Image (cartoon, rainbow over all chains, first blue to last red):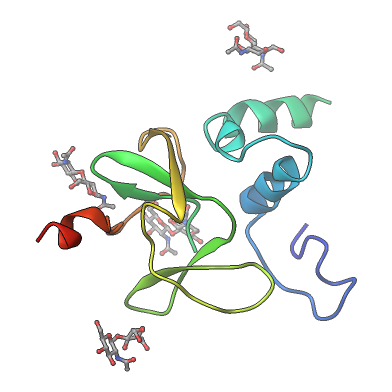
Length: 49
Length: 70
Ligand SMILES: *[C@@H]1O[C@H](CO)[C@@H](O[C@@H]2O[C@H](CO)[C@@H](O)[C@H](O)[C@H]2NC(C)=O)[C@H](O)[C@H]1NC(C)=O
Ligand SMILES: *[C@@H]1O[C@H](CO)[C@@H](O[C@@H]2O[C@H](CO)[C@@H](O)[C@H](O)[C@H]2NC(C)=O)[C@H](O)[C@H]1NC(C)=O
Ligand SMILES: *[C@@H]1O[C@H](CO)[C@@H](O[C@@H]2O[C@H](CO)[C@@H](O)[C@H](O)[C@H]2NC(C)=O)[C@H](O)[C@H]1NC(C)=O
Ligand SMILES: *[C@@H]1O[C@H](CO)[C@@H](O[C@@H]2O[C@H](CO)[C@@H](O)[C@H](O)[C@H]2NC(C)=O)[C@H](O)[C@H]1NC(C)=O
């Protein structure tokens, strides 16, 4: 949650979480603007799920 | 850091990399090695307006065209 996937390859590197989720969308073929303009929706959907 | 940069009322997002600030100026870097470059219109792409991104910051994005045309 605080370091993403960096602590498993060396030192833990902090990065804000909203920016971690944007990287993770990029890794599946979705552009990052789709998350940042819908951040509230994805957080609501995750919390209910 | 900041997710996007505002210029001319438009939101700019990095193609690859993250925005960083050294204390006084902002740069674009690649994510795996610190190597800053100036934020230009060839480094970024535009999507949406600066009203939906939380944490967007003001900066200058330089266009190479105008200083070539003096
Ligand atoms: C994408 O789908 C979601 C539902 O999966 C839509 O969000 C819902 O919208 C309805 C109608 O406004 C609301 O009553 C619900 O409360 C919303 N759900 C959540 C979890 O927020 C969303 O509007 C859709 N997006 C678009 C652009 O149509
Ligand atoms: C952040 O980096 C910049 C660029 O290196 C520093 O700003 C100065 O920028 C001018 C050009 O606009 C250069 O001619 C100077 O040599 C730069 N100074 C230095 C010390 O590099 C700026 O000082 C840096 N900020 C901090 C807080 O270190
Ligand atoms: C990050 O969190 C800090 C608090 O830990 C936020 O700082 C506050 O900002 C508000 C305005 O948004 C001020 O009214 C408060 O006085 C600030 N608090 C402190 C302790 O200085 C900061 O805004 C947050 N950053 C983002 C991008 O949301
Ligand atoms: C970033 O720059 C924009 C553009 O100058 C700022 O938008 C202005 O915001 C002020 C209030 O702070 C309004 O009075 C102006 O009408 C706005 N200008 C326009 C053209 O809409 C924005 O506030 C700046 N952001 C920060 C954090 O300073």
